[PDB]
Image (cartoon, rainbow, N blue to C red):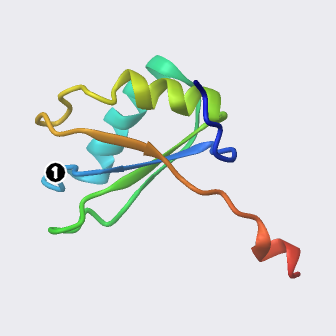
Amino acid sequence: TPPHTEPSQVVLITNINPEVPKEKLQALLYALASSQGDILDIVVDLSDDNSGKAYIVFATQESAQAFVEAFQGYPFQGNPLVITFSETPQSQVAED
């Protein structure tokens, strides 16, 4: 029963241990990502101390949802791994 809530070629991940640098962390996010769908660009926050999050951009919602559901409940970098979609607006260009 696919609800279909707008397109999303990007996914937002959280609850990630900032103990690991984006250099290594990102490298891992890509390995797993590729295992499911193709990656167009993997973004990562500044590895805060209370935030610790990132965003993995895939080819399309098809691949994203595949990886999100494929790892929706899998122990990564510890155990508590959360994976969800995100928003991809385009008004910044519409206005000008």
**Residue drawn 83% across and 73% down?**
93
Estimate the x, y position of residue 56 in percent, counting from the top left: 48, 44
Count of number-bearing discs: 1
Asked whether the viewer can see residue 8, the reply is: yes
If the image is split into quadrants, where does the C terminus sit?
A: bottom right
Residue 1 vs 22, above or below: the answer is above
**Residue drawn 16% across and 68% down?**
50
Estimate the x, y position of residue 13 in percent, counting from the top left: 36, 48
Q: Residue furthest top?
A: 35
**Residue type marked 1:** Asn
Residue 45 vs 95, above or below: the answer is above
Q: Nearer the viewer, residue 29 or 66?
A: 66
**Residue drawn 61% across and 35% down?**
3
Q: Nearer the viewer, residue 35 or 72?
A: 72
Q: Residues within 10 Å of mark 1 (few under 14, many from 20)?
A: many
If the image is split into quadrants, where does the N terminus sit?
A: top right
Asked whether the viewer can see residue 33, the reply is: no
On screen, residue 53 versus residue 58, left or right, reads left
Estimate the x, y position of residue 85 in percent, counting from the top left: 50, 45
Please, what secondary structure does the residue beneath circle 1 have?
A: loop
On screen, residue 47 versus residue 66, left or right, reads left
Q: Residue furthest bottom?
A: 95
**Residue drawn 70% across and 63% down?**
89
Residue 40 vs 66, above or below: the answer is below
Q: Residue furthest front?
A: 1
Q: Which residue is mark 1?
A: 17
On screen, residue 51 versus residue 45, left or right, reads left
Estimate the x, y position of residue 34 in percent, counting from the top left: 48, 23
